[PDB]
Amino acid sequence: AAQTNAPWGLARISSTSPGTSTYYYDESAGQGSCVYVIDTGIEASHPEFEGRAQMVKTYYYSSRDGNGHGTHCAGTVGSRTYGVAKKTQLFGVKVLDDNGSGQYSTIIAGMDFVASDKNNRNCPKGVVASLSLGGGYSSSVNSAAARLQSSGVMVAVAAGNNNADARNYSPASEPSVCTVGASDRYDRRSSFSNYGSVLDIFGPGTDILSTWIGGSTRSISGTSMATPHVAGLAAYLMTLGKTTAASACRYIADTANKGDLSNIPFGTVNLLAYNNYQA
Image (cartoon, rainbow, N blue to C red; front, side):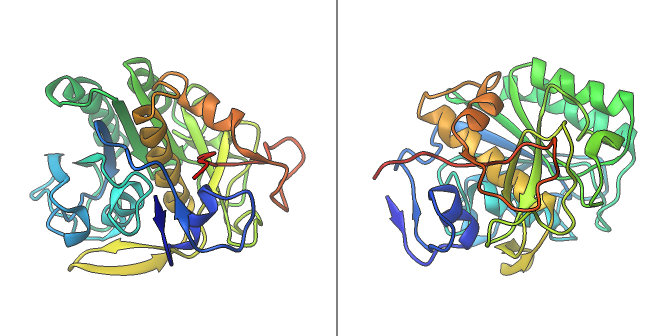
């Protein structure tokens, strides 16, 4: 399938070169997979989600996304126009308040929630969790992400936006999950992207158009935007049968575009997420 005039990041993930604008992908499109977006919520009524999104858990007075961040990330996972995996099922878990903040204890509870809740959902092709959040190093936060991964969920987490080594942030620093840095449309490391040996992969993160609250759209930047590209890619590849939740991060690294990014510090992987789709 071909989506013309796609957001640059979608075009990038199906291309051996920057500078194109059509997204190419297998029509299976993540059908039969599920992606949990653990964030500020998801505006599931947005026409872009086509009834495939729902809130399943909140720790606050509403499950609504009063911020926009979670809706934007969910749109990059799976919206019809802005999403990587256009037929996945999206499940929102609201661990962040409408200011975008959240206690680590709530975030941990949300991760353990997903590890159990997947047993209440129909995801025959597999389960992914996208975590566009983080703070300073916490062994307990890392351990929660490790449990979620161990339980059979492909966990993708943001590297962070500090232009610093991600070893000092959580859950970015957990070795067993997929830690995602950000790149721009010219294949440069995004100016804010964290780096370091703990990164597994880069995805598009600068000037990413996606869904927003109030039935709208906007372009924003962050490793928060790169992470759902990778989460959606994992769901797409799992639906194709090419990999599993336990092996998808490694498979994405195996099949990535290699050596094409600029300003990657010595010791950080130079790998850009790529679907290897041959139309």
